[PDB]
Amino acid sequence: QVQLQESGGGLVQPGGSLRLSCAASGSIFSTNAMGWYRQAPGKQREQVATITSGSSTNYADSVKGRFTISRDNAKNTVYLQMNSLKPEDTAVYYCNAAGATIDLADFGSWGQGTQVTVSSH
Amino acid sequence: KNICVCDFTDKLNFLPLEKTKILCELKPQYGEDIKIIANKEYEINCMNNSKVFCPLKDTFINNTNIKLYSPKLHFEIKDITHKGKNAALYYLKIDEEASDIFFSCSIKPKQVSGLLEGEVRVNLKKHINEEYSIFNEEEDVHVCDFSKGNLDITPSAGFYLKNSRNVSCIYRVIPNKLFLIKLPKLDIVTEKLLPSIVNCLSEFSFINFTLKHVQEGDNYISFNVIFGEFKKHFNLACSLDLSDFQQEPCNLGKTANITFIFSKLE
Ligand SMILES: *[C@@H]1O[C@H](CO)[C@@H](O[C@@H]2O[C@H](CO)[C@@H](O)[C@H](O)[C@H]2NC(C)=O)[C@H](O)[C@H]1NC(C)=O
Ligand SMILES: *[C@@H]1O[C@H](CO)[C@@H](O[C@@H]2O[C@H](CO)[C@@H](O)[C@H](O)[C@H]2NC(C)=O)[C@H](O)[C@H]1NC(C)=O
Ligand SMILES: *[C@@H]1O[C@H](CO)[C@@H](O)[C@H](O)[C@H]1NC(C)=O
Ligand SMILES: *[C@@H]1O[C@H](CO)[C@@H](O)[C@H](O)[C@H]1NC(C)=O
Image (cartoon, rainbow over all chains, first blue to last red; front, side, top):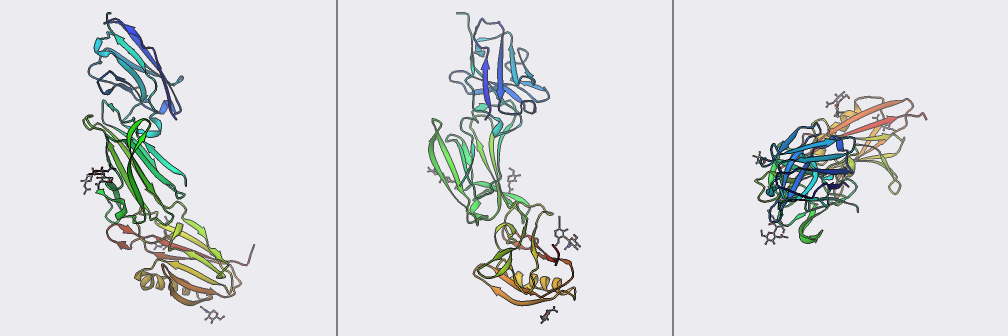
């Protein structure tokens, strides 16, 4: 069973920066593509960024140039560096497997996620 | 019975960046049953609406009932509550005598622009293709059974590649004992397979055999052969080929290979 644990969220001012971390266990991490996901109230969960086992990245159009996804194979961790944050980026952020074809055994039950709130007040 | 589970509940709930397939492959063996679970709101095409491989035409048939190709399978489709959600349960029970089949199920969430799909692939097929003959103590006979079980050569919809339709039974010849070759109850068995075993056994003049009876049972045809005493070592291989025998709409048979070991050693 794949276990996922996100951290690093919090309250940030518009235009500020934040770095999310996700520890994944239960699978052979270095052979899997990984991704960051987010869900705001009343919106569907969306895949925001993906990174292949070979570190090829892809991003949602709304975060291109502002978010950077990276991975540390030695620690089985995925990272999401978020600069120039906008209120529309407010959501609970989750990480999980990604890729064009995913073994169901590699797609873990969703972790608790980490809340990101972008507001002035 | 053990149960193989593909649980997609709350795992097809995102909009991906590119087309994404989440795949659950099942290779049920030891009489195992299968459960497929997904959120009720997902669009599911499974078992009574599956994609089935058709060996005879070497294609896949879409939107079809798996019972058309493996008639002894039975399944039920229920609404259940699972992980706090309203979910659908597809419960397939695989009896011991169910014939081989290769089918897939699709699970598509809505409003993802078709970019996310779940898929189950069920490959039911034999995995032991070589056995020794089995002694029936009550009948006092050694049997090579190609009419059912692992060495079944009956036409089926099993996903076998062209070079993988051989099954093998090994009979260590016991002098003066009756030996039974059990075959499917088909006209082709006596028309062509019986000439095959006769020509195989009679090819070498020094092999002593007697064909006793060609017998029709309730669900098999048997060739009854008695081998007499022998002295020298010899290995004889006979092929009873139904790998090209067709049966509409999708079934193809297998090739039964019998290895007769004549040995007074060990
Ligand atoms: C496959 O079987 C399922 C279950 O019997 C069918 O789903 C039913 O569909 C009818 C109308 O289409 C509904 O009124 C029932 O409530 C459904 N049952 C369940 C348990 O959801 C489904 O239509 C069948 N598919 C095909 C292609 O025959
Ligand atoms: C499957 O069995 C067939 C027997 O029907 C094999 O074909 C025979 O191979 C032997 C050599 O091992 C030849 O002497 C025969 O002439 C062949 N017979 C026919 C009808 O072709 C075949 O090689 C087997 N396939 C595999 C992959 O083992
Ligand atoms: C079945 O589905 C496949 C792939 O979705 C498609 O190529 C084919 O045309 C469909 N119809 C038949 C009869 O195979
Ligand atoms: C085998 O031996 C028996 C006698 O024991 C004989 O009747 C039979 O014809 C023999 N079979 C062959 C093939 O020579």
